[PDB]
Image: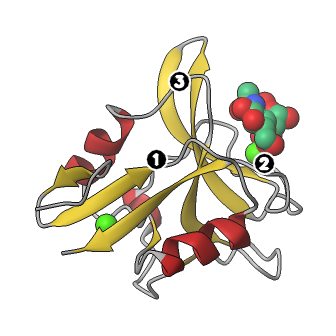
Amino acid sequence: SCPKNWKSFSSNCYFISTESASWQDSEKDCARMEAHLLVINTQEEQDFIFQNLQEESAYFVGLSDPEGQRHWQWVDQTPYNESSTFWHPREPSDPNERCVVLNFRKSPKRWGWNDVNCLGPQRSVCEMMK
Ligand SMILES: CC(=O)N[C@H]1[C@H](O[C@H]2[C@@H](O)[C@H](O)[C@@H](CO)O[C@@H]2O)O[C@H](CO)[C@@H](O)[C@@H]1O
Ligand SMILES: [Ca+2]
Ligand SMILES: [Ca+2]
């Protein structure tokens, strides 16, 4: 049973942020609640998260590229398989955008990933293992 104000899925719990913070301060805050930033593992997990996000907002996810070499890593250290990614067309787009967000686009309407800046505050998704 997930806590108050935490969406439930499979055997895990998810918190969709309303406040904004940098990628590191987002992972810092997920850790304070004994969780990590979201780590998309299956197609079903991703679609469940999209159903609870605001199309007008971007959401930080535990996927980053620290050195800027497009070496993507998950916070929970699990392997990255590009074929199971939800990158928008044109994305990733810039070596200096080192952190992945879930964002919605209007033409055409599509949920997907986008590498954006890490310091610029955004919303985030914490994933807690129950
Ligand atoms: C349209 C879009 O995704 N805007 C987001 C914006 O994006 C940058 C850049 O990261 C994208 O690769 C390109 C794609 O055209 O658009 C912009 O130049 O980043 C913002 C945060 O940095 C998001 O809030 C916007 O949603
Ligand atoms: Ca997960
Ligand atoms: Ca981008």
The residue tagged 3 is 55
Please state the horizontal and vertical placement of residue 96, each as a whole percent of the image. Answer: 89, 62
Q: CA distance from mark 3 to mark 1?
A: 16 Å
Quadrant the C terminus occupies: bottom left
Residue farthest to the top, as pictured = 107
Q: Amino acid at mark 3?
A: Glu
Please state the horizontal and vertical placement of residue 3, each as a whole percent of the image. Answer: 24, 60
Residue farthest to the bottom, as pictured = 77
Mark 3 lies within 8 Å of ligand 1 (Cβ measured): no
Please state the horizontal and vertical placement of residue 56, each as a whole percent of the image. Answer: 61, 23
112 in relation to 71, above or below: above
The residue tagged 2 is 93
Mark 1 lies within 8 Å of ligand 2 (Cβ measured): no
Residue positioned 32% across, 47% down in the render: 5
Toward the viewer: 119 or 19?
A: 19
For mark 1, give the secondary structure: loop
- Tell which quarter ligand 2 is in: bottom left
For mark 3, give the secondary structure: loop
Which of disc 3 and disc 2 is earlier in sequence?
A: 3
The answer to whether mark 2 and mark 3 are in CB contact below 8 A is no
Colouring scheme applied when the structure was drawn: secondary structure
Q: CA distance from mark 2 to mark 3?
A: 21 Å
Crowding around mark 3 (Cα neighbors within 10 Å: few <14, some 14 to 19, many 20+) is: some
Which of disc 1 and disc 3 is earlier in sequence?
A: 3
User: What's the mark number on residue 86?
Assistant: 1
Please state the horizontal and vertical placement of residue 79, each as a whole percent of the image. Answer: 41, 82
Nearer the camera: disc 2 or disc 3: 3
Residue 95 shown left or right of residue 122 in the figure:
right
Q: Amino acid at mark 1?
A: Phe
Toward the viewer: 36 or 66?
A: 36
